[PDB]
Amino acid sequence: SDLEALRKKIEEVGMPEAVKTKALKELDRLERMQQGSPEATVARTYLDWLTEVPWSKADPEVLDINHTRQVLDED
Amino acid sequence: YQLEAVKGTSDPAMLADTIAYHATWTVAEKQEILELTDLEARLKKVLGLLSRDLERFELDKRVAQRVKEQMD
């Protein structure tokens, strides 16, 4: 279940290079024959913590003062 | 017994698709094998997934020998 979904949500789910490195190091740390070490179990937790961390999903930002004014006027 | 019905038997699509269900690995990769209509690429995909699992378990027995020499 999660062993196959978390294997493939490392490299197509967009993720920064500081975080893609640990996602790949837990791709290599896990998937080791269903590793049963306690660090592998908390890494099974941690890889789920480190893939649904939201990246490659920015939403459009505005660098003008005029649109900055009126949205907080609506707020 | 599964090899006796495929060795010396025609229809290599039979021979690929019958054993692509029987062995247990990632189900989505089995469905992708069903998606792959190229027969030679299907046989090579089965061989490559077999090679991936074989090198996984050769690394298993290598690290197991590391653990054995480590406990010695």
Image (cartoon, grey):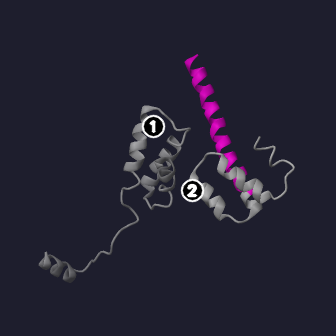
Q: Quadrant of residue A42?
A: top left
Q: Nearer the viewer, residue A24 or B53?
A: B53
Q: Position of residue B42 (x, y in %)?
A: 72, 58
Residue at image x 73%, y 60%? Answer: B41
As drawn, B36 above or below A48 = below
- The amino acid at mark 1 is Ala
Q: Secondary structure at mark 2?
A: helix
Residue at the disc numbered 2? B28
Quick check: B34 left or right of A5?
right
Q: Does the magenta-highlighted stretch encompass residue B12? A: no
Classed neighbour count for the residue bearing mark 1: other residues with Cα under 10 Å, few (<14), some (14–19), many (≥20) = some
Q: Quadrant of residue A75?
A: bottom left
Q: Secondary structure at mark 1?
A: helix
Classed neighbour count for the residue bearing mark 2: other residues with Cα under 10 Å, few (<14), some (14–19), many (≥20) = few
Residue at the disc numbered 1? A40
Protein chain holding label 1: A
Q: Position of residue B4 (x, y in %)?
A: 81, 43
- The amino acid at mark 2 is Ala
- Quarter the C terminus of chain B occupies: top right
- Quarter the N terminus of chain B occupies: top right
Q: Which residues are magenta?
A: B43-72
Q: Nearer the viewer, residue B49 or B10?
A: B10
